[PDB]
């Protein structure tokens, strides 16, 4: 276990205060669908027609 | 029949009115479609290639919507009655040359406003009466205006005998006094003519005229002998050719704008208006306003044609459907 931990590097701080770091992510999205409705506002069932 | 547009005009033919989108089977079948809340109105029409839908009309942005009876678009053919006035002389005076003039406002092939004349000569002798004068003046007019040499006269000449008083006796460049054997001719009528029409090249158009009489000496005084009164028309020119051109032009707003330009490399559009039928028209002017900062109006119009059968049945049903759907209060014909 010592040879295990002696592999990872060590980093020195100045205090024992909570530190945080910023995380950078991704952009390209697509939006789900809650539902759809006809021209009269009725909801589209799964057995419905075109 | 290139026209002026409030940024667009679209034409759809109501060859048949159907109740649902499923019944659109033949080209020309149409159905007005509006939601139950009556927020938008649109039309589903069967083109030769599948059903097409019109633009959607926000029923709050409708500027006006009126329909026509197909009698408003008809052009009555103007016809005068020529006669020598009993004031100067109730019968021709010998030795004097009677020269009649037909003052046309355009040439035969042009539409620009010009002065264009055609003449008719008659020289009166000791025994010539009124009948013989009208006869010879009519034949002179025919031989002078019916020198078309390609197509057709510019006006039509007839004679009325006092016995008939209603039966126009036609006169052509071939007629001769031997064919005209009456003795009670009392006037000459000169009607307008339906000029050549081509679908998208030659618009329907007429050339009005006025019978003008030159001066004769009767008692040493130069005087005018004629009476060019305007009797009521009896013939008409329907809108079939006029509507067909409307379609030809307004189908380039949703279809192909070129029409024969790159003749081998073209797209040919099928047209559903039957030139020869009489259509009663409907029109709906509306606009699109837009969002924040975009208040400028894009005004538009959708017009619909339908054959008239006397009573404007087809259009009356079409508007009844549109009023039932969009709640509008369009008036019937």
Image (tube, rainbow, N blue to C red):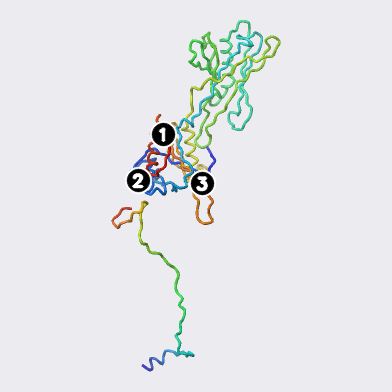
Q: CA distance from mark 3 to mark 1?
A: 27 Å
Q: Which residue bears the numbered disc 1?
A: B307
Q: In the picture, which quadrant includes the C terminus of chain B?
A: top left
Residue A16 against residue B195 in the figure, above or below:
below
User: Can residue B4 be seen at all in this image of the molecule?
Assistant: yes
Q: Which residue bears the numbered disc 3?
A: B299
Tell me, yes or no, whether the two marked residues, 2 and 1, touch with CB atoms within 8 Å: no
Percent position of residue B33, x then y = 38, 46
Residue at 59% in and 32% down: B111
Q: SS for tag 1?
A: strand
Q: Nearer the viewer, residue B144 or B71?
A: B71
The answer to whether marks 2 and 1 sit on the same chain is yes
Q: SS for tag 3?
A: strand
The answer to whether marks 3 and 1 sit on the same chain is yes
Q: Which residue bears the numbered disc 2?
A: B21
User: Seen from this angle, which residue lies furthest top?
Assistant: B127
User: Can residue B55 be seen at all in this image of the molecule?
Assistant: no
In the rendered structure, which disc, 3 or 1, sits on the residue that comes first in sequence? 3
Q: CA distance from mark 3 to mark 2?
A: 27 Å
Percent position of residue B264, x then y = 50, 44
Residue B128 against residue A46 in the figure, above or below:
above
The image's mark for residue B283 is: none
Q: SS for tag 2?
A: helix
Residue B203 against residue B143 in the figure, above or below:
below
């Amino acid at each position: 276990l010592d040879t295990f931990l002696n592999s990872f590097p060590t980093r020195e701080f100045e205090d024992d205060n909570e530190y945080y770091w910023d995380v950078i992510g991704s952009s390209r999205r697509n939006i789900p669908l809650v539902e759809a409705r006809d021209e009269n506002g009725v909801v589209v069932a799964a057995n419905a027609a075109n | 029949m290139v026209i002026s547009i409030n940024q667009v005009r679209q034409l759809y033919v109501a060859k048949a009115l159907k109740a649902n989108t499923a019944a659109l089977t033949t080209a020309g079948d149409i159905v007005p479609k509006a939601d139950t809340a009556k927020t938008t109105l649109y039309f589903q029409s069967m083109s030769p290639a599948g059903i097409v839908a019109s633009d959607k009309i926000n029923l709050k942005h409708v500027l006006y919507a009126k329909a026509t009876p197909s009698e408003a678009l008809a052009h009555k053919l103007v016809r005068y009655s020529v006669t020598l006035d009993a004031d100067v002389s109730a019968t021709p005076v010998a030795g004097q040359n009677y020269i009649l003039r037909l003052a046309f406002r355009q040439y035969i092939g042009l539409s620009e406003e010009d002065q264009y004349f055609k003449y008719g000569e008659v020289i009166a002798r000791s025994g010539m009466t009124a009948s013989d004068f009208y006869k010879k003046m009519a034949i002179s007019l025919a031989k002078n205006l019916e020198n078309k040499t390609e197509s057709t006269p510019l006006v039509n000449i007839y004679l009325i005998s006092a016995a008939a008083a209603s039966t126009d006796v036609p006169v052509t460049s071939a007629t001769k006094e031997s064919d005209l054997t009456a003795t009670d001719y009392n006037q000459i009528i000169i009607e307008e003519t339906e000029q050549p029409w081509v679908l998208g090249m030659m618009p329907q158009a007429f050339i009005p005229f006025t019978p003008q009489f030159l001066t004769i000496t009767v008692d040493g005084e130069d005087r005018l002998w004629g009476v060019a009164t305007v009797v009521t028309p009896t013939k008409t020119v329907p809108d079939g050719h006029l509507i067909a051109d409307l379609e030809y032009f307004c189908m380039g707003a949703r279809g192909d704008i070129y029409r024969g330009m790159g003749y081998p490399n073209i797209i040919k559009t099928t047209y559903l208006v039957d030139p020869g039928a009489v259509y009663d028209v409907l029109d709906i002017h509306y606009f699109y306003t837009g969002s924040n900062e975009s208040v400028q109006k894009s005004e538009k119009t959708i017009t619909l044609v339908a054959v008239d059968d006397g009573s404007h049945t087809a259009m009356n049903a079409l508007i009844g459907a549109i009023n039932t759907a969009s709640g509008l209060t369009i008036a019937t014909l």
